[PDB]
Length: 241
Image 1: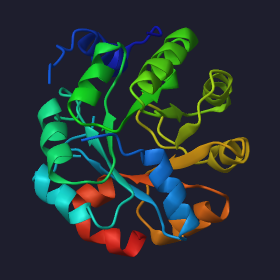
Image 2 (image 1 turned 90 degrees about the vertical axis):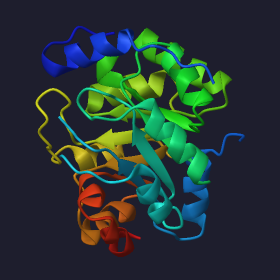
Image 3 (image 1 turned 60 degrees about the vertical axis):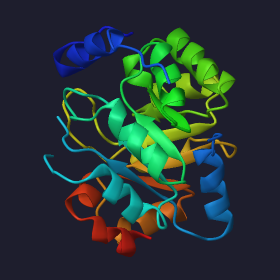
Image 4 (image 1 turned 90 degrees about the horizontal axis):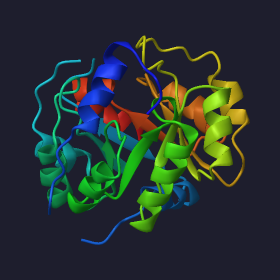
């Protein structure tokens, strides 16, 4: 991984030691989004997470069932220490619903992607700020050999530059600085404008308003990853969709 300090360094050290886990074909999240775009349907990816470095108690299976007929897909937190998730959330949800599942964790080795796949995930997130460029490209290719097209998280012009050169086709534009936790949307529109035509673009959020989703979609954004506000009030999905 990259050199890190604070909670990032701690979470990556943990992930490097993540025990692997021996265990329905893939439904592409990327594809589904495209198809939702072609039908003029707002594509929301609802995030399940109990905590965030948020503290909600909500059943994973009920949440996923509730979201099932609305969302383009579900991202599930499997990171155990800061987000209070586990592989078992992913396992139960992937067995309970039939929409694409994105496994959200801090992926630093190959075995975590084996885990994603054997747990029933259709895709994974990879984070440009966590990894060297060579590690990113290697893990992207590893996920592809399983038939997963990963969503690569970018944060700035540097992130995108590396993501594009290694051949990413699916990109999450995050406005969160992972270290400081602060959300800054000021480079968001310019980042979105720099993404090529052939890439499926997801905005990651601190999204809570329909209005904001509409402005973004006008700019060409393909889908919307939404966490905190859905965890606080699942019912908001209706306004967003």
